[PDB]
Length: 479
Ligand SMILES: [Mg+2]
Image (cartoon, rainbow, N blue to C red; front, top):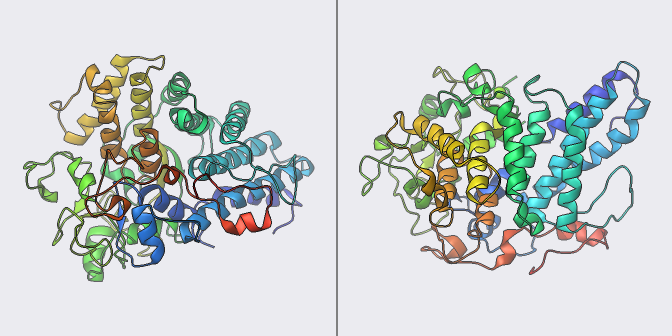
């Protein structure tokens, strides 16, 4: 698209690569987030589009589904850009730090392949070294192995942790490895819980801290507030001075008066799409658990708007945004001082792709499942999260809690801590509860009370779009 020539062009080329996550151009962050939340127990979408039902229910086929196309095209676009960048970078002028730029381009490509591996399993494998009109996929395990070797090799050449908010630093590479290793039994058939713990410790030792205020993690000024910057390892950056994060926020608001929307959210518009299931609400403690009300919640992590809404989605998932399912206002374009962000549409709120709260929970789960690490520390990390949640010391857990009921307390706690941060689908797959009939939620499988679905649905199908033009590429099993 833009040829490489002077120093500026190489710096702008790297920035274009990083920018694909935030870019509309639909948007990678939105598509990815949708695909990680909408088929789960965390979110159901009230839009009437045929794709929404399919994704809501997990009844999709190989018929084209717009967010599936989005995630796939945009990830492979990142890979394309990085490959062209790496091909040009040896000709860079002397003023460019080639070693740093190569390490960072490679991080972006590794992350794009991570998302593809987790979501599609078997993408085409195309690097700057194996150019082909019709590239073949690796096995999922081989792709994992390649991504891991990319991240291990580049890590000592990446910037030091926190040296620039938004840049893929050494700790960002370790956070991605932690997330890969936690899930390695899914991707590779072999568990890597010790390696998960090792990557978590690399992050923990870099001096990150939990934000004092949980809610501010997801407000307009999360990227500028020092309290929340202590915790955010890797953000997808947004600023009012692209519709990706705007769509996630606005999508979760209803058709209310502009002023009431601005009052409570810092936005003009509410598209009446994304909202909660009963399962998400019931994960949190309330003053009266038999009759939950958003204003009586005890675990303050749950940030809900309940006016006029039932807890359950019962009659229909579409057309019922205003009446069935609580709204989720976790991501907000009000700043931490209550003021609106500087634009009513183009939000300031950053997406926290990796943050220390997740690292804590990963460390605890990896130790629970038998990795080499400390149960005492695991308990300390979960209790830090729960003290923040409840504002007191009366909701601590103990070591037995980590292992009991087949690690389900950890799945529940990742729900309470990390809901709507784009990780729920991966976590459900790890517990093999995404597709199973043993754990159901509102409209799972297309039945209101919920049913299991076939195990093919643990991954999305590769676009027929790409299968038509690439003869070496194969569809995922079962589709
Ligand atoms: Mg921002």
